[PDB]
Amino acid sequence: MVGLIWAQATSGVIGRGGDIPWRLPEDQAHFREITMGHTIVMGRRTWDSLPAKVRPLPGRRNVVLSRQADFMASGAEVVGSLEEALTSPETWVIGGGQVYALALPYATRCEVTEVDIGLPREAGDALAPVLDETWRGETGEWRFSRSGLRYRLYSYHRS
Ligand SMILES: NC(=O)C1=CN([C@@H]2O[C@H](COP(=O)(O)OP(=O)(O)OC[C@H]3O[C@@H](n4cnc5c(N)ncnc54)[C@H](OP(=O)(O)O)[C@@H]3O)[C@@H](O)[C@H]2O)C=CC1
Ligand SMILES: CCc1nc(N)nc(N)c1C#C[C@H](C)c1cc(OC)cc(-c2ccc(C(=O)O)cc2)c1
Image (tube, rainbow, N blue to C red; front, side):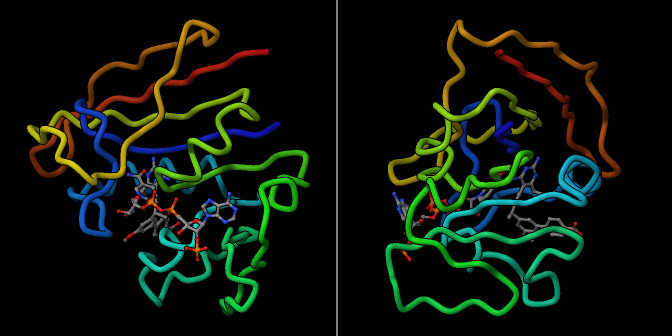
């Protein structure tokens, strides 16, 4: 089972300028709940965006995709191909834009957080993948953050 997990603005934006363009603690707990104890796979750019205190993400086997055979990352398994990255029975792909696109055909689950923020797409943004009709989805009820942000969770499956 390969799953994708991401948080997006309604527009589809998941990243801009190498960061996630909002703060949503409740989403972080959700992310932790889904991924804990499992292998997580991420692109090198997403690995870089992790704060040092949380790099590698603890309690998870961190796998980082890079075409750089040189690339070093303490606490992470650096691999040069997707095949090398998806060798765990339950694998969660945690970003970013490039790697969601690469892993999407391998995926049978998506766990999506939608953030109700005004954030129209700009050229060069990292974007969420588009889920087509092969997917079946359940839409969660809207929640309000601490904070000021409305958000909701989707669970998507295909067999
Ligand atoms: N909102 C969310 O849920 C999330 C948001 N983000 C955001 O996403 C953005 C980063 O995503 P993105 O810019 O798309 O970059 P990625 O995080 O997807 O990493 C891209 C890198 O992955 C490596 N790579 C890509 N394809 C391959 C391949 N086929 N084989 C081997 N290595 C490969 C390369 O690393 P190299 O260049 O070293 O070869 C490439 O530069 C940031 O803004 C981040 O904050 C990230 C995760 C989740
Ligand atoms: C929490 C954000 C997030 N939400 C969802 N639903 N899917 C995702 N794939 C990511 C993501 C991501 C990137 C890798 C990221 C960036 C970041 O910048 C501060 C922090 C985290 C992060 C995730 C979990 C934990 C934790 O378990 O304590 C800490 C930091 C994770």
